Image (cartoon, rainbow over all chains, first blue to last red; front, side, top):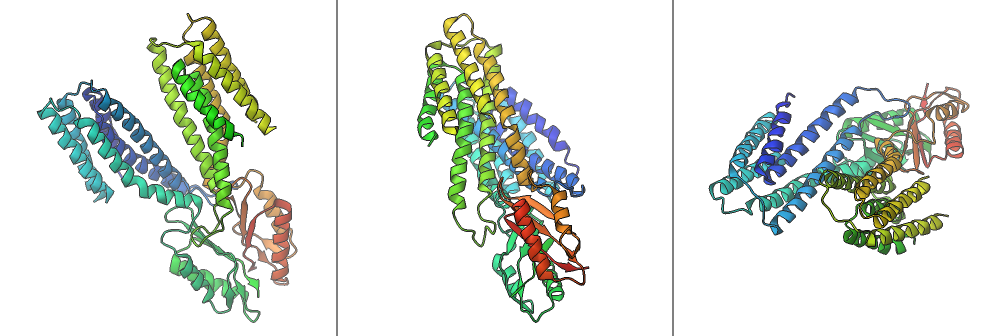
Length: 258
Length: 258
């Protein structure tokens, strides 16, 4: 929608965390980076979807959603690994200056940004909200008692782990879509039984089910009808069944003879 | 079994570059990592492809090649970016100790390893030879004249650029395959004309051409035959034409009526 203020609110963590010399605010910025990367990928995909399919892209540009999601996950692991290495160095070499002031202000900025994002949404968004509250609590802990100093790297560790756990399922879905498995919603067996219940169909040879993206599903089959049947009627009835029951965007059914 | 002897050789790059405190050895190791990942993914993809297709993966596991290639490219950019940042830091902060007493030996190990890989292969092999020779020349310059010190970062920059330029085309091919475009070898127009030249076919509605991997191609169509035609004969002739001319692994042609 109009979530452009999240990008300027991103800048607060980058500079404010620099002054504070903090890593928990870096994990807050990494979570925000994953969110804004998902939003930017969705916007770019929506812009690309209106473009018609060319002679070199026979399906269109519906894989941009999955590619953008994969890129966002890769960048999130970028930041997570960098912060993991930095925190591991920080722990052993216990020589770094952290001031709780800038930490507290930028953590407050982060929690209000998360509240605005939650309002816009109105899951792992609430999970992240909890993570932002944890970072804010760590900021109070550091600022109030400066003698404590290892609060920052431990929060970095826990919240990076939380980020990885939260975005694991998206990685799984993207991987399955890219490897061209059956879509999550659609089961192979219900589709096969639907195909065989068409009057005339005797067997199906090569039933292919795959998804271009989360909402775009394609199908193919090799139905073999009984000789005393009308291929056009059988094909039309099977396509209507697929469209009505499973919402397949495309359905190419080769009708052979038994 | 090329990497059966260059995986241990890769170990010498990491330790040898550690003692030498060098970054050109890191770019040599990055090129070796790209090659290692590429054909290790090839081996893993073959081992996955020998498995049959399940109810979940209706097309089999032929996308593992593309996924492994993408992972290898991502890891190469990992190393390249890390080395870019390290070299940029090393340039303006000109305070580091580099000795050729390990640089020269590790560069020699790298060049003999690259020669052995070229023999095994017996294209970017000549680029790899040139880059390894450049690293070796930088090592000779550093060891012979210790007063020069900025040789390491500049070579790091040039050979990182060489690596990125060399693996750009693989990234482009992987991106096209994942976005489900027409394969490079197969042209949309020749396939369409082949389909329309079948006796009986009037027009094709939805011609879909896409590739599971580099060597696996799939096709679909919606041929609309003449009233006075035999659908089975037309379908068989079209499938045989596709298989013989374009080598399509699968061909699902829906035969409608005009």
